[PDB]
């Protein structure tokens, strides 16, 4: 995908985004347990 | 398709059942597998299981009862390796 959380956080930053941000491929794979492939 | 990859996520306290968090075919499948290798996520080839999951369980959906036994087996491998 083309949207990363850091883009949102960077848009805000002093000040900072308190609420959490969806859903990137990288974030999903990093936390995943196992990949099943053909 | 030529290539299929299914990313499964199971974490006590977070997921009541294993969750298909990402799925892909062709270029997107190759991507998932390369990112899996980068992040040291175990990758297992099982052609019938990959095909059935791809057809039946969509991104963001929990696996259904027909998949409990084969998927749980893989989750147990991952727990062992971790």
Image (spheres, rainbow, N blue to C red):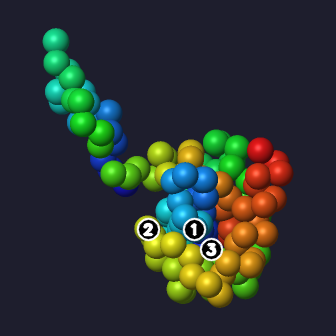
Residue at position x 53%, y 86% in the image: B56
N-term-proximal mark, 2 vs 3:
3
Residue at position x 29%, y 43% in the image: A21
Check residue B60 in the rendering and tell me which mark sits there, or answer none.
Answer: 2
Tell which subunit mark 2 falls on: B
Q: Where residue A16 appears, x then y in whole percent? A: 21, 23
Quarter in which the C terminus of chain B is drawn? top right
Tell which subunit mark 1 falls on: B
Dots 2 and 3 on the same chain: yes
Residue A26 vertical position relative to residue A8 in the rendered view, above or below: below
Q: Residues within 10 Å of mark 1 (few under 14, many from 20)?
A: some
- Answer whether residue B45 is visible to the viewer in this image: no
Say which of B47 and B16 sits in front. Answer: B16
Check residue B17 in the rendering and tell me which mark sits there, or answer none.
Answer: 1
Looking at the image, is mark 2 or mark 1 nearer the viewer?
A: 1
Q: CA distance from mark 1 to mark 3?
A: 25 Å
Say which of A4 and A28 sits in front. Answer: A28
Q: CA distance from mark 2 to mark 3?
A: 20 Å
Dots 2 and 1 on the same chain: yes
């Amino acid at each position: 995908g083309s949207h990363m959380a850091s883009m949102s956080k960077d848009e805000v930053k002093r000040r900072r985004l308190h609420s959490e941000i969806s859903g990137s491929l990288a974030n999903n794979i990093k936390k995943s347990t196992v990949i099943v492939k053909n | 398709p030529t290539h299929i990859a299914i990313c499964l996520y199971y974490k006590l306290g977070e997921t009541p059942l294993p969750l298909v968090i990402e799925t892909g075919k062709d270029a997107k499948a190759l991507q998932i597998i390369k990112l899996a290798e980068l992040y040291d996520i175990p990758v297992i080839e099982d052609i019938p299981l990959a095909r059935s999951l791809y057809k039946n369980i969509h991104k963001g959906q929990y696996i259904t009862e027909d998949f409990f036994e084969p998927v749980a087996q893989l989750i147990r491998i991952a727990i062992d390796l971790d």
